[PDB]
Image: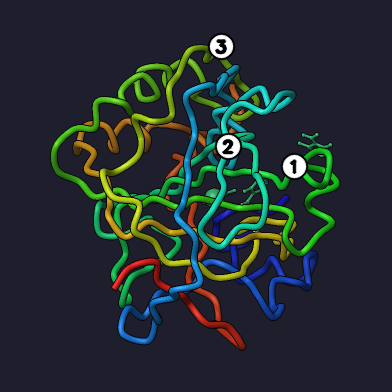
């Protein structure tokens, strides 16, 4: 099955998932000079006070921190979004070196990692019906650079050694995702897709301009995870990013002048 290796990575995915060569695939490069400020964008609202985290899972591609989405609790609204979107999970993508790791790029610059907070449109009942719709999902994307440690990331880092291999999970209650946000909510937005198979074209992307800073030690611990399962040869979980895809007939809009 699919992955990030030479033999099963991004350049192969189109054979099982033809939408890989679709009209609104992600990630993309954000050309900051071509992005236009959009005065029609409403204020973004990220309301995480009631977020209820449950569990952290190594899925053999990344780790997911999963939330209880059975009530209206951690929601994203405003900006380009119509209505209310409910947080279901977050995960990251990162490199084998600090010079690469993000999926979106900014004027071709790769960050060391990228965080995705995934939300589904509450008009559609749950996530599974939301991914049948062209406005089913909203993903808040946040770049990570290497510098000072991010304190609100450390409880994630400290549980990783308990989910080293594919299929492992751990309790991960009482985690506050507010600690992963930068100060500013300035963002770029465009319509795109999931970035791993099944690559579905359901996502309103909201990519924050301000990166968060994490320490070298925090990202080095991400790189100790494994793609493999327990007992199998070690293949370190690094470089689990899809590169930029053609923009096609899309415009990237800025929330800021
Ligand atoms: O993601 C993977 O499945 C993978 C491999 O199976 C082998 C090397 C690198 C890699 O990312
Ligand atoms: O969360 C859900 O309700 C869900 C999924 O997370 C995946 C598939 C179907 C579905 O309803
Ligand atoms: O690729 C993704 O972006 C993705 C999600 O964001 C949520 C669930 C599955 C998935 O592949
Ligand atoms: Zn992702």
Please state if 143 lies on the left or on the right of 166 as rendered: left
Q: Position of residue 230 (x, y in %)?
A: 59, 22
User: What residue is rendered at 39% in x and 30% in y?
Assistant: 178
Question: Residue 75 — which label?
Answer: 2
Disc 3 to disc 1: CB gap under 8 Å: no
User: What residue is rendered at 54% in x and 70% in y?
Assistant: 190
User: What residue is rendered at 60% in x and 17% in y?
Assistant: 54
Disc 3 to disc 2: CB gap under 8 Å: no
Does the beta carbon of the residue at mark 1 sit less than 8 Å from ligand 2?
A: no
Q: Secondary structure at mark 1?
A: helix
Residue placed under numbered mark 3 in the picture: 171
Q: Position of residue 207 (x, y in %)?
A: 43, 59
> How far apart are the alpha carbons under marks 2 and 1?
10 Å
**Comes first in the chain, label 3 or label 1:** 1
Question: Residue 84's quadrant in the figure?
Answer: top right
Question: Residue 148 — which label?
Answer: none
Q: Does 26 sit above or below residue 216?
A: below
> How far apart are the alpha carbons under marks 3 and 2?
22 Å
Q: Position of residue 179 (x, y in %)?
A: 34, 29
Question: Label 1: how many residues lie within 10 Å, few (<14), some (14-19) or many (20+)?
Answer: some
Question: Residue 122 — which label?
Answer: 1
Mark closer to the observer (3, 1) = 1
**Comes first in the chain, label 2 or label 1:** 2
């Amino acid at each position: 099955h699919w992955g990030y290796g030479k033999h099963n990575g991004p350049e192969h995915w189109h054979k099982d998932f033809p939408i890989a060569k679709g009209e609104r695939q992600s990630p993309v490069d954000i050309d900051t000079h071509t992005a236009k400020y959009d005065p029609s964008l409403k204020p973004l609202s990220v309301s995480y006070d009631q977020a209820t985290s449950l569990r952290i899972l190594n899925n053999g591609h990344a780790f997911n921190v999963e939330f209880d989405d059975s009530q209206d609790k951690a929601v994203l609204k405003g900006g380009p979004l119509d209505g209310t979107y409910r947080l279901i999970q977050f995960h990251f993508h990162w490199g084998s070196l600090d010079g690469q790791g993000s999926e979106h790029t900014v004027d071709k610059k790769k960050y060391a990692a990228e965080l995705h907070l995934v939300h589904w449109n509450t008009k559609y009942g749950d996530f599974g019906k939301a991914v049948q719709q062209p406005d089913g999902l909203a993903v808040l994307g946040i770049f990570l650079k290497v510098g000072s440690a991010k304190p609100g990331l450390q409880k994630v880092v400290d549980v990783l050694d308990s989910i080293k291999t594919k299929g492992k999970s751990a309790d991960f209650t009482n985690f506050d995702p507010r600690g992963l946000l930068p100060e500013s909510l300035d963002y770029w937005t465009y319509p795109g897709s999931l970035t791993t198979p099944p690559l579905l074209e359901c996502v309103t992307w909201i990519v924050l301009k301000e990166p968060i800073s994490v320490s070298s030690e925090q990202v080095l611990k991400f790189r100790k995870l494994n793609f493999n399962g327990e007992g199998e040869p070690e293949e370190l979980m690094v470089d689990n990013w899809r590169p930029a895809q053609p923009l096609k007939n899309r415009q990237i809009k800025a929330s800021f002048k």
